[PDB]
Structures are given as C-alpha cells and as structure tokens.
Image (cartoon, rainbow over all chains, first blue to last red; front, side, top):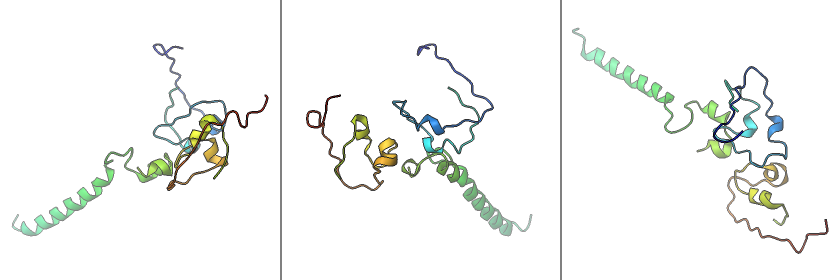
Length: 50
Length: 49
Length: 49
C-alpha cells in the first residue's frame, strides 16, 4: 500500500517467533525502539500492530 | 484529642515513609519504573541510559 | 586490528551496536577508547566477477 492509505493488520492470539526476523540477511534496516531485537523472544506482548 | 503531640510525630514518620515508598513508582524520564521491565526489554548498551 | 569487511557492515563497527559483524565476526566493547579508520579499497582487491 501507499503511505497515505497504509494497511494496519491487528495481530491476535498466536505464538510469535522473532528468531528468524533479524537473523536473516533479507532486511536492510531493523531499527528497534523501546525494545531490543535480542529480547523479543522473551517478551509476551499484549497487541502487535503491523 | 489530648495526645496530639505524640500522634503528630507518628503521622509525620508514616507520611515520610509512604512518600519514600511511592517514589519508587515514578519514572524520572525513563520508560518504566520497574528495573526488571527495563533489563528484560533493552540491551546493556541502551539500558544504562 | 586489520580486517576487511563490505560497505555498510564497515560502518557497523562501534561500541554498543547491533548487527551481523558485531554479533559473530568482530565485537567492540562498550568502553572502547580508540579510533576506527576505514577507507575505500576498490582497485587493489577487486577480482573479475
């Protein structure tokens, strides 16, 4: 989508696996804010918004 | 209400202790008051700040 | 410390920084008191293909 009409997918009950999201040479930038990418496999979030 | 000078000291000490305890809930500019929530979310390079 | 890396990964040499090189190739402590010198080297190493 564009930047003026951007999709917003509401994540729900699941078991996220942030293991292969950063350990994969397919992303140019993986800047995190407020959290560290190495601690995402230990945190249980309430609601994720993509 | 006669024993007021003795109750005032106890009330002041209790209020001082209550304020000192409630001061542990402030953030002081940080992202969270609990240190465990900071040590479990950020890395040592960014957790010191 | 002489070593060769590629492009943006060379700019990934800094105290307290995440990345591929810092993870397993070459890690820099968060106390590093020195200097990181890097220069482009195209026509001294580049082979055909």
